[PDB]
Image (cartoon, coloured by chain):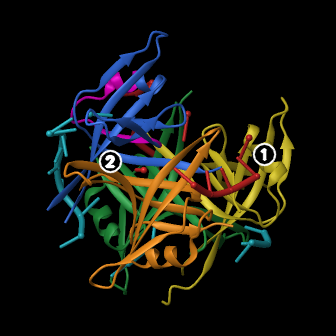
Chain colours: A yellow, B green, C blue, D orange, E cyan, F red
Amino acid sequence: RGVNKVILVGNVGGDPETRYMPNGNAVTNITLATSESWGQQQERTEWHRVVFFGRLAEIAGEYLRKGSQVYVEGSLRTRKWQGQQDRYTTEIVVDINGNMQLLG
Amino acid sequence: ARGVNKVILVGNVGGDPETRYMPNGNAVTNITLATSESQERTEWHRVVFFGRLAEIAGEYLRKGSQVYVEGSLRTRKWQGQDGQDRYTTEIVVDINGNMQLLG
Amino acid sequence: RGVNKVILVGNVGGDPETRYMPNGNAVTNITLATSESWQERTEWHRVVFFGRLAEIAGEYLRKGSQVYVEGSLRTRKWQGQDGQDRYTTEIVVDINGNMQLLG
Amino acid sequence: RGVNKVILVGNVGGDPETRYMPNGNAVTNITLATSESERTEWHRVVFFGRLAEIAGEYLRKGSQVYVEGSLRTRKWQGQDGQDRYTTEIVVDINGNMQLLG
DNA sequence: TTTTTTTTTTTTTT
DNA sequence: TTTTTTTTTTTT
């Protein structure tokens, strides 16, 4: 029994990168900036790695541009890769269980 | 705050919590949190409590406790001992967040 | 386009009621209490489950169960026996929602 | 112990209504439409405190807005002397509001 | 068309 | 009492 939910509203950092997998499913990557309040309650930007799959990846690939404001709802997944050694990347995964809404 | 940055987790604590205090009065509690889905899949989460909830967290949470956590994502950069850049994404729970012991 | 999300953690008011429609689909109703303290203050929520979650909720929830519910708000209009309009806002948990029995 | 959280993104139905309590505190009411495909759902959202001032100052008919609050079902006496209940989304110090666009 | 439960009293860009 | 165009049962 568990719950793994991420909700972000922010601005797309650069144009989305769409790839295709072995069966042809669209996979779209973006970076997303959210602004929090960093002792004078200042400003600070947090950058999020967001990966879409399926129809949302298609929709994100087509309508999201650099600077787009977007609502994103997904689940956290930490991916383990290795370089030359062990590395980790925490991403927000947006698939059938998630949601995306182009705002503006 | 111009964006929204919200994380909601329900899961099981991976080990007894580590609390620590500094010369600010602040309590800082660190835990790991397992969320699962069903093959059966498990995701491991690093969660850091600050302030009042840090005090509440250190006391009542124990290895295996079930807990609701609401916080915000924060990625910290650090140079490893090989000089190479690394990143740690944590869930930060403070005054704008929430914690609820379950069971 | 928009977003309509409700997240509740609370205690089930009574045993669920599960209704089966002529086509075999299930609808399960509960009430769910969430509280805040400062004196108590308990908010009662009407939660309706559809689909696979309706059968799961009907089978595993009982009076007093602690539960996580994720759904969407829906307000229904109806004329009362005095002839006047009334409204009932419910939390609808369907394929887009979630339910986790806690504790 | 429990959790009561509502997150909405939608469009304001009319210009906001703001009133002032005896202690000077602002209270702002809106209705907010969310849709899904196509059926539209209407929500009664009530802002308190600083967010109520911001809401009253910046929201207008048609504004797209993100809102985060708690559900509160309020009992009130109707125009005839019997009971009406209204479930509202209360947005206060524990909630959030963001103008979108 | 009532209930539950119980150890937590100032949210555009990478 | 009207706004706005594509989610069944764990312990690092």
Q: Quick check: D8 left or right of C80?
A: right
C80 versus D77 height, above or below = above
Chain at tag 1: A
**Hey, what amino acid is under mark 2?**
Ser
Instruction: Say few, some or many: other residues with alpha carbon within 10 Å of mark 1 (under 14 / 14 to 19 / 20 or more).
Output: some
**Residue at 43% across, 19% down:** C26
Nearest the camera: B78 or C33? C33
Which kind of residue does numbered mark 1 sit on? Answer: Ile
Find residue D13 and report its horizontal and vertical position in percent. 55, 59
In this rendered view, identify the residue nearer to me: B12 or C30. C30
From the top left corner, tell me how far across and down residue A20 is, in percent.
85, 39
Q: Where is residue D91, by image quadrant?
A: bottom left
Tell me residue A48's x, y (percent). Answer: 66, 62
Image quarter in which the C terminus of chain D is found: bottom right
Which residue occupies 29% across, 41% down? C32
Could you say which is closer to the camera, residue C92 or residue B22?
Answer: C92
Magenta region includes residue B49: no
* Residue beneath disc 2: B65
Q: Give the range drawn in magenta.
A: C55-72
Please tell me whether residue B8 is drawn above or below residue D95 in the rendered image: above
- Taking the image as shown, residue D18 lies to the left or right of residue D38, namely left
Where residue D12 appears, as percent x and y from the top left, is 56, 61
Q: Which chain contains the residue that carries disc 2? A: B
Judge left or right: residue C90 versus residue B44: left
Residue wearing tag 1: A59
